Image (cartoon, rainbow over all chains, first blue to last red; front, side):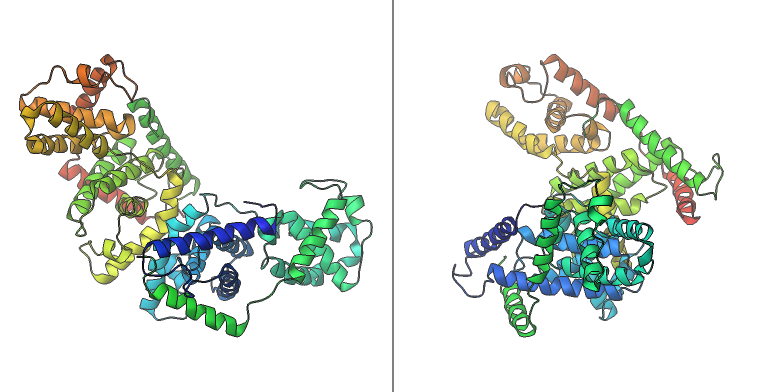
Amino acid sequence: WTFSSEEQLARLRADANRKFRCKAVANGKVLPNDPVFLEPHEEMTLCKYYEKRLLEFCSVFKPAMPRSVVGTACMYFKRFYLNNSVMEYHPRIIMLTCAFLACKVDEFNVSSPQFVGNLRESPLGQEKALEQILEYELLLIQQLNFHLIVHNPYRPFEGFLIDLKTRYPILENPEILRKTADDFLNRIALTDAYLLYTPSQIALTAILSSASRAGITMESYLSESLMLKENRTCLSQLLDIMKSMRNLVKKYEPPRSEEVAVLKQKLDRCHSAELAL
Amino acid sequence: WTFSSEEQLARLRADANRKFRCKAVANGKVLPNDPVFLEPHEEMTLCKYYEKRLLEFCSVFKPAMPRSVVGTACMYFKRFYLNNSVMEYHPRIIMLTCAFLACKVDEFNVSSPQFVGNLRESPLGQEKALEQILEYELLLIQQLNFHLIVHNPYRPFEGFLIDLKTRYPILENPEILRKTADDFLNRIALTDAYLLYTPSQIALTAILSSASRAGITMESYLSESLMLKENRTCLSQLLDIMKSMRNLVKKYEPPRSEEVAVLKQKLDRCHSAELAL
């Protein structure tokens, strides 16, 4: 569950898209080239959109949801779709299933009625969503190969922040660093970076690249402090990895208002006709 | 998930009982020798009772539930409690969670509202049960070590029945054999036999021991047909294994009406006071 390239994820996602196309066509009600089907690239936009809808949900989640939970939930959502089609299991539901499962896994103390209680729908509407999470729970757990422990960036982040503040007492005002570094971490979390690097490299990139966004530079930081090494890197590599992630977020295209509007409708029209009977 | 003795399961169950006692006592509200706690032997009675309540539920389950499902569900229930206390997770709920998970795992086509629809409770009461299954789903899956595939006796049973009817055309009236052998299989399913032997040995014992209950004896059956061997046994062992299971069901003490009434009340009084805060 930590891959070697954007190409490797591209392939997996493509496979998932074909597998459904073939299943749908196999179950007769549609021709192989029917434009009802979403293209891998279209699935992606919808996933970007839902991952954002996922983030919003967690942000407003009244019983204040810890960042370990929101991070875990997003990792699930991503991994699910590396080999599953948006056309087969609706991401509106899978998204909410990832949040719930994540609360359970991370032992975040919240009951299901409390959880669905955070949805802007009538009491029965919310009960209905609770029902759908029961439907997809095992599916989600199975599609994750039963590997539910996900290591988030927030832990090594707090550690790097600690390292800096005691090592460079000048910046004893990290309250500014943290907020910036958090903003940047959120952007990385929206790319495939979580599936591509260690959470430490991810935490490190958020901090060094945010302090730097601020102007300040600790030219002796990596060398002096990080003579130590936990996640594979003779300094140089790390510098390239940071350049790599820093690039990923630079080239991240957010879902656009209207395309989503179209693709949602396609996705809805897809779940509408029995393609999966 | 196939053990070497009733002693091995006895130990596991005992451990589970102590672990809770210690957790409860650790969380202060109770003394180590408080009679509120159930003894391992008492847990057992309650489990026998619930496994029967489990069987009844599946029997009346309107969208006719296949025997693979009911068998799988009972295996879960048993395995859950090999290392978990009835005092900690109520078997009324775990029982229903095992049924649901089993429908999902075996791909028995039934939705959650359909499932809970089979409970003799008001619409909200049933929704409440659906909620509790969502609560315990992951727990159940985790406590099963993520091993959800359970091989039932019904498959090799149908095969042995086929073997007999073509090999001894006299008994071409197996409709009688089957019903008897099924009745006996139900009795084995209530003992630890499922956790102790292969489903083939279990299927074989149900058939050979039921034909025999009927009077008829095929002295050339094992030797002539079963020169073949899939599950460890130089004839002799098998004969001893059949003697073993045949013994287990002989010495199975069903839960008694009033003791249950008491133990339920103890169990309820247990879940009543916060022992698990």
